[PDB]
Amino acid sequence: DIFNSPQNKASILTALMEDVLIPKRFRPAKDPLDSPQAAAQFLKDNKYRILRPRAIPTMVELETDAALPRLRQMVEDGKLKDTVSVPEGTTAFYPKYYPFHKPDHDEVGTFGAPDITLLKQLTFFLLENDFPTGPETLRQVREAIATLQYGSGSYSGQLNRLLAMKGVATGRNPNKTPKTVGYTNEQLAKLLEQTLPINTPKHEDPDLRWAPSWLINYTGDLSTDKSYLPHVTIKSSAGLPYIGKTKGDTTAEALVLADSFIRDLGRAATSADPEAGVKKTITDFWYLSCGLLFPKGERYTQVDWDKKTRNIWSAPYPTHLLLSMVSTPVMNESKLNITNTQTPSLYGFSPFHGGMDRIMTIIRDSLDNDEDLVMIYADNIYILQDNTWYSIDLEKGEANCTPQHMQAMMYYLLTRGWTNEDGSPRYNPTWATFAMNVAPSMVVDSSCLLMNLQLKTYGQGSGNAFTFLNNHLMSTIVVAEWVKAGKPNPMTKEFMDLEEKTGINFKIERELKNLRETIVEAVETAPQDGYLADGSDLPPIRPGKAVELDLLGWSAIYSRQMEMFVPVLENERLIASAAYPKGLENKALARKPGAEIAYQIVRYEAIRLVGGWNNPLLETAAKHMSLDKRKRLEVKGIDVTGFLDDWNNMSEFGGDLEGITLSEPLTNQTLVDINTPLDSFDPKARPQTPRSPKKTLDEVTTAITSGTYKDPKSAVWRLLDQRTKLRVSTLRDQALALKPASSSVDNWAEATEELAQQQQLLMKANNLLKSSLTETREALETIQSDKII
């Protein structure tokens, strides 16, 4: 007996405890900053502000019908918990927040696992198919698996991120308030009328006059039972004072705290001593300004794992609720962007249903007419000039925000949104006080919690209800300054000089040269074969050239079948998402077997839908995998159609492609359906902005340089601007000045004008002039004497 197949004999030591094609799992390094002592020393060494820790009173159980009288019937019907847990204890506690960082040095598991199954399938399919693009697709997917890692970073990554935020806010280019840049609240509002056009909330929506719990209508009758409050993610964190609880566990508690904060603020504002009362309320509710520093799940670079972890500033549920009551009713009625309105705004943009083709038409018309073009989306700016497409991103956007930026946004929302047709306010002095005087210092330049450490937040908390709005306002200032400077080319020093002028850090992320010629090429190289070409259910052998705009992560591809540009996910994103697919993170659906099962198909269909369809190797492998899974289910008689119809609520690409079904496999018709426009497009037929319709951003900028719009014409708006300059002690007098307009009394307009005349008499008193935002921060950071556990 000779010639037996050799087997690897190893030592007993080896037994007791290389493939180039498959990369080994990434094991994060040991984190030296994983202790409060080490983290605090690191921050102290790096001159990052650590606040004197404030404590929260211990929880006390109260009767729900006593705390929330509006919801007595809900308690009586056994539909709402009979007791609420509120921080009203005699003893206090210091809060601690210890987030989970996965994968970590000790645990490299299922979470953040790369799609090795897909990698193997891509390899097998490449061996059987002569796709010209195939070898590069495989190499890129393998490289993304080898260089990236999906996960929640590390304590070191989070701490280093915080340092970078301090650097943006106070380092090379220190932040500047809009006033410092040269804009009054009214001048900014005139710019925002163009860059962020808004409509008023619905006439049936409640005005900003009530305690949150009053906006809940409960009787028992399902046809009439309604909540006029913003919607919340039930499974998301409650934030302070309920660490380790979800919003679902604490809605009654959040209502109690939100009602109390707004009610107490209101009472204090009109009291005998508004300064002492307002400061006391702010100090008592300090925790409403402190976010939990949550590590964001992303496809981080392995080598930079401990250098950068993006954070989500997890806002206290009551604060989130109160802020959302101001923003959401306005924004829900304001899905106005460049594809439907004459505005640079990209708010509510979707590249699907002809959206990308509308952008391409606007780009082509601008190129043909030798016109410059600008588009704004939060911290993203797009400039078309000199036959070049530029993508400009604010450098760590949130860090550039000052409380004054948010106050200017609140001014814009309350003047252009929360207003009646007659010019009377859709708010009372209590809500004007919260919105203008307190709210901006609760989420901007406030604090965050990591472990037992209460740390300073430099700029706005990323993830707060106003993140997009505040970032959009900052980009509006950068764009307005670019227009003022005579539109300098983004590659020049004249453009880069706008960093110091605005106090806003930014960088050129993309420079797409010879745009006109690139577009011609995209049209000419469009294939005659396959999906959206001859309409067959196959990828093209050789795909066409893409116009790599990276417009909110999208590139443009020309379709011969549809005779239009269609979106495809930017290559780098497509490859990263294929390499590290997110799990069923979406909702609390994770334990649902139907959802978990359907997701496996959803994952591969979504990657095809977003642009994989146009990559022959990726399309071949992903089609095979989804079909194989569907076949297994069909044969086995396991039905997951429900989850496949409502797949949007599970896929990271779900929001983008709403109302399409994955119960049937992806075909050419799926691609046709997602790209089908409801209406034909004429850029000239797009309605103008709701406010200053005939004016352009360029005209408003020119008017501002001439000193126009320093002060609003409306007396109501003048009182709201004066509100930003007057100290908290003046709150009772400011409430009196607003009461006639707020109550819509007979001849309120004349009365408001006379009251503003009276208030103007305070405005000679330099002693009465102090930002309520500074007073809020002082009160939030104050450390009053209390006995801890």
Image: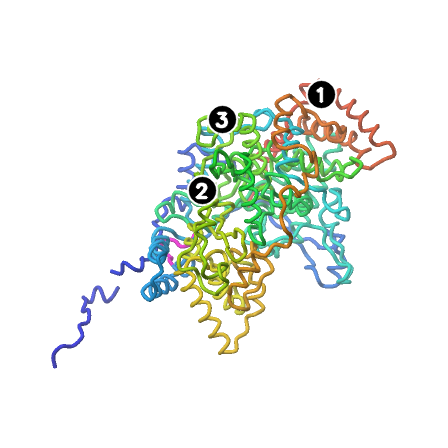
N-term-proximal mark, 2 vs 1: 2
Determine if residue 307 is in view.
Answer: yes
Q: Which element type, helix, strand or loop, lies under badge 2?
A: helix
Amino acid tagged 3: Glu
Could you tell me which residue is drawn at 21 percent across and 64 percent down?
13
Determine if residue 445 is in view.
Answer: no
Q: How many marks?
A: 3
Instruction: Nearest to the eye among marks 3 and 1: give it.
Output: 3
Instruction: Nearest to the eye among marks 2 and 1: give it.
Output: 2
Amino acid tagged 2: Glu
Whole-number angstrom distance, CA of label 3 to CA of label 1:
31 Å
Could you tell me which residue is drawn at 69 percent across and 29 percent down?
721
Residue 350's label in the rendered image is none
Looking at the image, residue 409 lies above or below residue 529:
above
The residue singled out by tag 1 in the image is 763
Please check the rendered image and state whether residue 106 is part of the magenta-colored stretch, yes or no.
Answer: yes
Closer to us: 326 or 71: 326
How would you classify the magenta stretch by its main secondary structure? Answer: loop
Image location of residue 485, percent across then percent down = 53, 25
Whole-number angstrom distance, CA of label 3 to CA of label 2:
35 Å
Closer to us: 608 or 2: 608
Instruction: Nearest to the eye among marks 3 and 2: give it.
Output: 2
The residue singled out by tag 3 in the image is 500
Specify start and end residues of the magenta stretch as a single range: 101-108
Closer to us: 365 or 483: 365
- Residue 356 relative to residue 758: left or right: left
